[PDB]
Length: 77
Image (cartoon, rainbow, N blue to C red; front, side):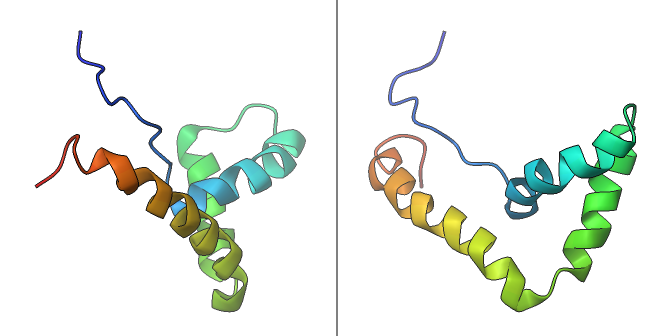
């Protein structure tokens, strides 16, 4: 069992986006394949204007500073 500084690890950028566009499609598609889910999202995301990706990259960047804040002592260089 290894769980000392066990902090909170964030997901990927487009992931924070998946949860957002994951119920819409999966909603109209109650039975998507992990491939379709992530692809469809990978498609919309890819299409999502860069200026629109800001909130997501930004959100992750905010909590990132807080994360690596103490994890440094944990897994690190």
